Image (tube, rainbow over all chains, first blue to last red):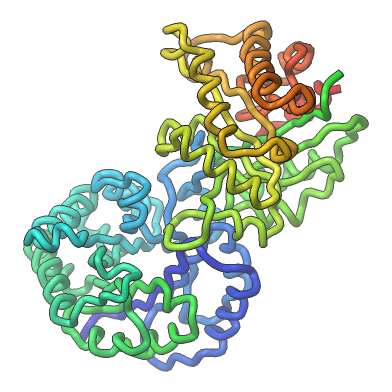
Length: 249
Length: 249
């Protein structure tokens, strides 16, 4: 079969106590008969609320970033503080962090290795920018990015990793990648993994699609052979999210 | 005659619910008889616990950083979000932020302007490094730092501003700043404000020392004319912070 899908809500830098609670009541009331792991990535400020109010057994709370070690880094949150707080999932390498907060492939590779070592389940994000896609650099970019992460990880380390493919050009622009494009980027990444890591690994690996996924387009994307779930922005702030969940099995 | 002082605990990237809750306790049991504003800047993750537990009438909580607007900034936390959460104080432009996280003078100044626009009381941070210092550039750097923040505020805005001078040259370098030196950097700032903004603003402005402060050197530092409190790193995670508050008598 396919490995257990994932339907992850990335709330980004948004919400209010009230708006978010709403969402959570919504989610908590939802029924999900199939095997799927739902993840809610809230801002650090609202990790308390969520963790207290989110009761659905199929959902887990996640952070949206972190640094590897506690210390003199004013403004940042480290993995240790996260763990102590009860958080076991984290999103790392987000294109927004890469494009605006100087996160290079190394920096990402590192946070991931560290996160893995501290025992977290990590969603690592990889993907090309409009300009690279237009140059015909898709394969080199994605493969380089994955290989960066791969370096620091050990075989067994893979059981905690979930890869997120997100074509930067599909980010909050409405330009969703076609199922073809999506499946073609996922198969490539997956070939690399069985080639460099092992087919056993490539087979259990969850690879998500991110980039303007919505209630409507979810089903066809999910229908692809190498598409195991989704990493969702905007629609995740809507009840429509529920639809997204239902499209994966 | 000096304005009301401020004793600001910058917990930086540290803390565990256990250790933090104990400090809180200690802090709440403290008898402070003078007019001082005590601020506790915790990680984003700990804001809730912090809010619930601190009960001392003389304490307020603040955050270590923020972005101006909500949106597609994974990992980031904005003003509106903090505003809803009940946080009204913010530390901004911290030397650890300018060093490792790309905060230019221009970024810190827009961040300051937004916070002010939003009602926050802001602790804005400035200070030169060993090199600028070594080279005779102390005043040029400091003044540029203050001016940049100032080209976005109006006179009335200053009622919401607190400046913390950070002796970067003396941090992690092997060096030691004496009281006379803190004082010189502080007077310099005051004269610039006093001169570009107004003498009225100037005499009211709080300029906090952001260097190495312990329970032993606090009073002699407080003893200096243009010294209005401290922005404490390390000693804030220790009971010694209590001697730090008293030193503002």
